[PDB]
Image (cartoon, rainbow over all chains, first blue to last red; front, side, top):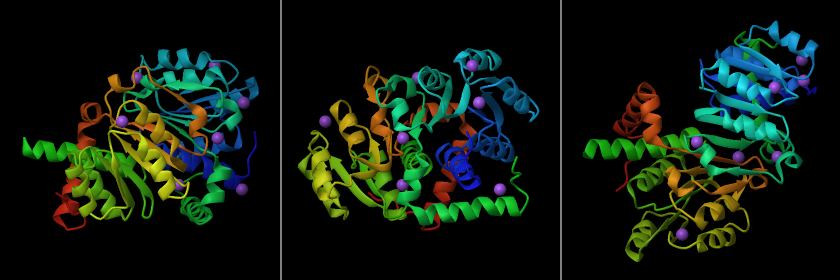
Length: 179
Length: 181
Ligand code: NA
Ligand code: NA
Ligand code: NA
Ligand code: NA
Ligand code: NA
Ligand code: NA
Ligand code: NA
């Protein structure tokens, strides 16, 4: 779904760069990638030079993604992306997941983390309140972090005003192309 | 052996507090078993950052050693009383970062005292939490749970960790990080 430019970019940069430590060559899975946050995430991932794996909910959205030159475009309405990506990666998986999918997608996305992997949950507390995670799934230096941008902005508005200026400098100096 | 011990302690504490934990000035960090090698590396790096340091240790003499370092709190690493104790001391706030090497009930009780935005860093080997589970509602206020296995990390990315250890040592050589004993 849509998000304003400031929400989309703050969410995607805090999630991929600060929490997710995304670095060149790493494999990132961005669910719902045609949405506001998803496209900010694909724009940032391209700046960093990560390998980009995506999903979306319609043929037309998926077609828009195949045109961006990414490694993988799967269906956000199914959990088939997990096996598809393991197949594609010869068992590696991905280094960071930026998740906005509900239910089985959370467990499957945690399952396909590589060693050192970072799972970032953007869903509302609703989505995972009942859910539990087995800590054995994080043992190979992996992590699970929730990002609630509304809360973060409420608690640290100065820090996020500064981060927005930082991100926009990258736009102004041509480092970050807004897609 | 001495050079290696120091590199493991400092790589563990710096990757955990600075890279994974994003520790920043004035944040509250809980360092368990703070008189151990990694624990002391983390106290030293927390002092460099200007965090507010909460600690535990397992004897009276080790607790006294920590009280002499000038930290906010020294509690018992063999009890889960620290969780209530720190909530009382911080008037309900809890802590921003937990650097955990305790097994058992201390893992759930340290996750419960994370502030919003809090980061729990688990240093135990896998056998410590192999059948442990975490309700994800516990992470809802922008919180996170990260395992750090430095042995694994060194196998996987040796050049990156060589660069990090050089950075740390340069910081110490230049007086920016004081190694505490
Ligand atoms: Na705009
Ligand atoms: Na979609
Ligand atoms: Na799918
Ligand atoms: Na695992
Ligand atoms: Na205990
Ligand atoms: Na914070
Ligand atoms: Na949440």
